[PDB]
Length: 50
Length: 202
Length: 101
Length: 50
Image (tube, rainbow over all chains, first blue to last red; front, side):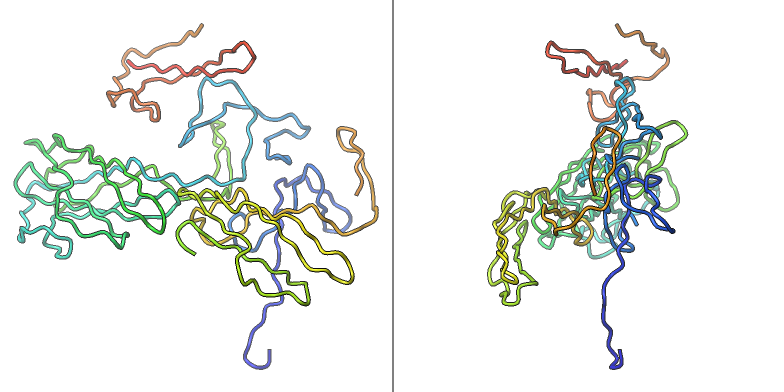
């Protein structure tokens, strides 16, 4: 910002799946969470598994 | 790798193999085949129990000048080694060990803590190392050491064995290796399969 | 607060007239190895919003291991509540369980 | 029945007392599975020390 300050507007979430090659495509370069594919299992950028 | 984290073929026929149990887990050779899974959960820390430390010592090691043994003056000891131990909650403690030479074929070993704020510097010898005329350890190579408490944790007494040591003029003195069977907690980060079918987690 | 003991406070950040937690909602007391013993569940109530009834429910912290896991990191959370919504599509799974979305 | 081949030239286990956690104290560990009356299988671990 214009007073030598910084702000945070949120964080990017990376949702690793317990099952790759099990996602389903519903259009453009985009998948949807389905059965036999895993729960969202959210997470931050650099923590561990990601 | 399906919903329940089970290794399975493209249709839904779960993979099978020898189950593994223990700590560290070992492949039960004759066990009945059972499904192989990949638990994403974390394994709890196991406190150090069997720490071992080899050392290469010298026959011509001079006697320390200052005979009052201490931990401040470097002249108080001939050799200094260090190992790491783990509490019951994954906290790491540092165990120092000092070797001094009074006369030939005889050495005095003193342990010391460096993480407990209430650990007073001792002078009592932890044990004695007795050596052959050729430089082979005789006895006194089994010790039990208990640490202190660190922020609400109970100590874990470990067996320290200076097995297969030697003092046969390796120039100076140096530790060959240090190890134990204790580890911190940690989460699953990667898995693989070796060329012998033993599935491996990291 | 001390060795093997934590205090748990709560706050509804959506209530316009909420109050900062003066006391502890509960207290977690841990086994020496790092196993949770007490303060497993606690009754928690929230405030009414837009003329709608408030929610009184249970909040549980079971199966929590404080064992020097690096730094602090929440492992999992779960509820059973959901916003009202409409149908989009159905399907038939591999065991005949016709389930909607 | 358990038919097993034993190596003649294998050495005596290092640790003289019989340990159950580490293999230094036993030569060969095998496992068979027997069945009880109710049907719950029991794993019989056999330990061989020369």
